[PDB]
Image: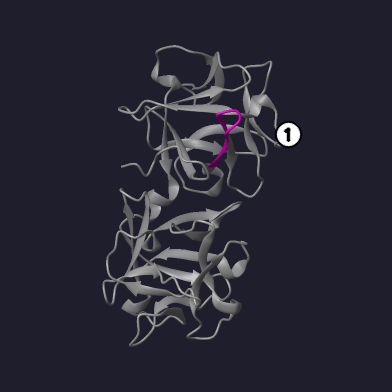
Amino acid sequence: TNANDLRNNEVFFISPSNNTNKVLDKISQSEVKLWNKLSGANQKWRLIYDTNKQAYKIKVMDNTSLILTWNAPLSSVSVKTDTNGDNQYWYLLQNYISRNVIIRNYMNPNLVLQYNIDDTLMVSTQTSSSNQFFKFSNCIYEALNNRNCKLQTQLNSDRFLSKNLNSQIIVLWQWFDSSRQKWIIEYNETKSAYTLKCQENNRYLTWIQNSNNYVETYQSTDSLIQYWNINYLDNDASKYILYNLQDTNRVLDVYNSQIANGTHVIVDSYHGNTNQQWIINLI
């Protein structure tokens, strides 16, 4: 799959190459360690790419906004407040075939992140050992791919993304355990984004481009209007934003932030308010 590619603005589990069941974990306010995979937000990391530097920040997703930091001149690493230090940027360079990634410090590219036998991390000069290889696993792909899900607006705990009765228009509706409110989320390798298929009619969440900008269930198409970048909110892994591929500045949104049954769901310019936030759960 290309779903685990080192894309800007995606969120990952970072594992030692020798153990897919351990992940980089912010255990305290400052310390990181490899730990049993639990999927808490303190084990999830957003990549923020700096094009000028060709290097990334690696930000924990537990709400603290702390970033992986080499404690120069020492060999220790920590999570620290982002002060844009050169020691806080990392090159992420991938072996295409093995999928292993070296995490190389920007300030001193002689040094790479290393995991030790005792599960601690440090920086070190480069060897040929697997203790300097990491695997990256996109969190959302792991959790949601090929799953039957429901999507709740943050606006109200009992209003869900629903195909309207006897029309293709997609609206908010209270839960009634209906196939019109159940969505199969599937990653499309070609578009590198998701489709969401309504269980009732086997048609897909699609931006219908006119002055209304409604979403409707629509037949399978290669057109970008049917494809969605499902992401966590920038600093909240408990909520989702869905950006449409036709215009990735536009997102799944609730018309006028209304909560009434039948309220139109639309695609509108990103602002990131609660009307654009969605709670996705497996059925």
Q: Please state if 273 lies on the left or on the right of 99 as rendered.
A: right
Q: The N terminus lies in which quarter of the figure?
A: top left
Q: The C terminus lies in which quarter of the figure?
A: bottom left
Q: How many marks?
A: 1
- Most foreground residue, 30 or 206: 206
Q: Residue at x 47, y 48 (%)?
A: 39
Residue furthest out toward the bottom = 166
> What stretch of residues is rendered in magenta?
46-56
- Graded by Cα atoms within 10 Å as few (under 14), some (14 to 19) or many (20 or more), the crowding at tag 1 reads few
Tell me, what colour scheme is on the image? one colour
The reply to whether the magenta stretch includes residue 160 is: no
Q: Is residue 98 above or below residue 250?
A: above
Q: Is residue 249 above or below residue 6?
A: below
Q: Please state if 74 lies on the left or on the right of 242 as rendered.
A: right
Question: What main secondary structure does the magenta stretch of the protein show?
Answer: strand
Residue 237, position as x, y percentages in the image = 54, 53
Residue 208, position as x, y percentages in the image = 41, 72
Query: Which residue does the numbered mark 1 point to in the structure image?
Result: 83
Residue furthest out toward the front = 210
Residue 226, position as x, y percentages in the image = 37, 63
As shown in the figure, which amino acid type bears the numbered disc 1? Thr
Q: Please state if 29 lies on the left or on the right of 216 as rendered.
A: right
Q: Find residue 53 and report its image quarter.
A: top right
The reply to whether the magenta stretch includes residue 52 is: yes
Q: Please state if 169 lies on the left or on the right of 109 as rendered.
A: left
Q: Is residue 133 above or below residue 66?
A: above
Secondary structure beneath dot 1 equals loop
Q: Residue at x 55, y 29 (%)?
A: 54
Residue 161, position as x, y percentages in the image = 44, 74
